[PDB]
Image: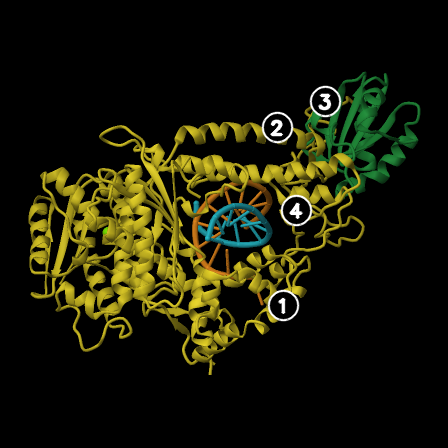
Chain colours: A green, B yellow, C cyan, D orange
Amino acid sequence: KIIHLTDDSFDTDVLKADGAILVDFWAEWCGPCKMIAPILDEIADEYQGKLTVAKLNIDQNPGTAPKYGIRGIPTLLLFKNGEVAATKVGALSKGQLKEFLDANL
Amino acid sequence: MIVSDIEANALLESVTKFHCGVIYDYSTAEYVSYRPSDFGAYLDALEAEVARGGLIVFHNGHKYDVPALTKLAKLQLNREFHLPRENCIDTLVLSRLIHSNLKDTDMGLLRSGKLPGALEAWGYRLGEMKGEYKDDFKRMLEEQGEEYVDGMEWWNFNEEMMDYNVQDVVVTKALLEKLLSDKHYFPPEIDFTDVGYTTFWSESLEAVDIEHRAAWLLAKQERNGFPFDTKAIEELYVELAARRSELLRKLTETFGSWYQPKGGTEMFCHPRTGKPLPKYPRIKTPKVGGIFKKPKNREPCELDTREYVAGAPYTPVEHVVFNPSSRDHIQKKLQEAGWVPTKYTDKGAPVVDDEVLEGVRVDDPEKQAAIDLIKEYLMIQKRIGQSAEGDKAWLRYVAEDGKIHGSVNPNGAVTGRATHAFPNLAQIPGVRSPYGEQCRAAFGAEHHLDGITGKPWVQAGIDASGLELRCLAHFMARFDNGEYAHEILNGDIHTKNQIAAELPTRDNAKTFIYGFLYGAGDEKIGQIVGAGKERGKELKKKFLENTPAIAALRESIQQTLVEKWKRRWIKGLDGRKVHVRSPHAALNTLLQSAGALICKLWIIKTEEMLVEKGLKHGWDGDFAYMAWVHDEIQVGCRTEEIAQVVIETAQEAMRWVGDHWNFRCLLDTEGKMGPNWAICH
DNA sequence: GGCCAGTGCCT
DNA sequence: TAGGCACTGGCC
Ligand SMILES: [Mg+2]
């Protein structure tokens, strides 16, 4: 259920998606990133219908992260109506993420 | 003989005030100090020693003390003071001759820590005096709640300064006696502290007189400077800078920026077990922050718009734009294009020089073309660095008289070769390389306008012809009776060697021999036949087998050194000891040493012959030495007629040198006239 | 600062 | 493991 984005599909998949979208900027060589990966699989599976999770590998798609000023990874950006609602950096826990969404959803 | 030293307010270029001086007289064994109001008496004491036909010893006096006294006497006393060359001894010049196997700080211009090997103690103390006096002065003020500035330590005369001056003379005297205790250069039956100048130069080894004459002449050359076209180089800079901007634009579009981990402190540890993962990038673990802001009164809290969550680790990262100057960035991008590195540096890292970049093949067409843009970018940075942005760039060194006054260590290499620096005028791009014509054209006598008539000067470029091969011919003459020499100046030495070696092209020979003379590596030798390191060693063996005279020469030199050494040095043409690092390097050291010494005596004799013809040396005269780059000299001349006399005189002097050292191969020179270095070479 | 790995420019 | 300078990058 997780959507895999690219630099070129970003604008339409996220910015013009009318609905809440949780984006995850990651990289294969980051420890914390591989930590939250399993978590996200579960979240996308639970919030089906209410939310959409999408990942963007910053090494294969280097032109998007800069536009949002990424300073650390994994970075989670909650988009809603093409605008960034909330932001959070770090390998959150299955519980911590659950609170973050419900509170901003 | 007297030993002296002076303290003034600045370097030669801008000195204006005499602070103090100290003289130690061997005939009375006493130290006399002279304060500022004693300048006139100081000078009279020196001229007296000259009236007795005595000697004055200064440490680095050829480049500073002597020229400074002339200048200060005119400025402060409106007096003409000119110490004759024959009456001056310089312990720095002597040290560089006798301790040629060692490096030096060059009077504190170079950082001790960077120079390899050991340093002569007395010489080290003399070179560190300024920096030492400066630290004493600072603490002095720093203690009196005062503030330190630039180099205020040199603005005024004071007692600490005088004390250091006295110390410099006791050390210079110690160095002197240590240097004069060397039997190879100074016969033991003679007390050199109790002889007149003529005995001193005549009874010591010939290299002593030669090095002192070279130092004196080269100091004058540094003072003359090399006329430089500032505007031309500024216009060249603009052009290079624009090309750089454009190459960067194209390369940043072809290669995109990426993210790199940066700023991590804590180590990442496997959450499952606990096994630290040293390979993974460092992370960071915030201690503050949460989904909701801490409560402050059932009722839902106020969300925390903070980006971090206590206990939730992340990897700090930075954005990095492709830098064409970074060999790492280049290495990173070419692999990610299909490049498989072959050669690596002996420290974990793929080699990425122009040599290999030329052989890199990737599938992407645009990526493959970018490589040529990268090689161009690197070369442009090299040129921009040398002419305008480097710490030693030409535009940073040009003086108000429109000239660059580069430094020269007359005896900076073991072989007797000179070294150039600040900036190194011996490494200006040649006309055959990119932008070389414009760089070379900016240096030249045409950029100097005569002081009286305003007319540009003319330049004479004079080169010793195939000097190294002739030296080789000379040394093999005792084994072949001059046949090799006879062939060089009569037959065709290059095809002769082409047959000696198994080379397909004559030019291959011109390249082979040249590499052989400076002792090129087996690899480069192979790279001429196409092969590498294999055909290399092979050729060198085939060449010698068909050139017995060279093999005999190499065998007798080795007999001189090895019996485990019998002696670790070779005798130069002037009698000096030339340290030999390795037996296999003996021949190369011998040849390189001969050319260096011949070139040194040659430029010395040329100037002495011009001055005997009535020509005056300097911009206020008829000619000016501007550059000496090993086998070649660039001479500025007030007129074309004078340039013709210089060229002709140089040939006469070169012949005088060959005769003087009974050279078994005729020596020659070739001269060219023109307005600048691009045309005169 | 300085310190240093890698390279290139001149003979 | 030609011999000398000197430049830029990357680091503690
Ligand atoms: Mg001094």
Q: Which of marks 2 and 4 is in front?
A: 2
| Disc on res. B246 | 2
Residue B157 visible to an observer of this rendering: no
Are there few (<14), some (14-19), or many (20+) residues within 10 Å of tag 3?
few
The kind of residue on which mark 1 rests is Lys
Query: Height in image: B276 above or below B78?
Result: below
Question: Of label 4 and label 1, which has the lower sequence position?
Answer: 4
The quarter holding residue B195 reads bottom left
Task: Please tell me the numbered disc located at residue B266.
Answer: 4
Is disc 2 placed on a helix, strand or loop? helix
Labels 2, 4: one chain: yes
Tag 3 or tag 4, which sits nearer the N-term? 4
- Residue A49 at what x, y percent from top left? 93, 23
Query: Tag 4's secondary structure?
Result: loop
- Return the residue at label 1: B537
The answer to whether the beta carbon of the residue marked 2 is less than 8 Å from any atom of ligand 1 is: no
Whether residue A21 sits left or right of residue A71 in the image: it is right
Give the x, y percent position of residue B656: 30, 60
Q: Which of B617 and B664 is in front in this view?
A: B664
Q: Where is residue B304, by image quadrant?
A: top right
The circle drawn on residue B302 is 3
Q: Label 3's element? A: loop
What residue is rendered at 42% in x and 68% in y? B474
Type of the residue with mark 4: Glu
C-alpha distance separating marks 2 and 4: 41 Å
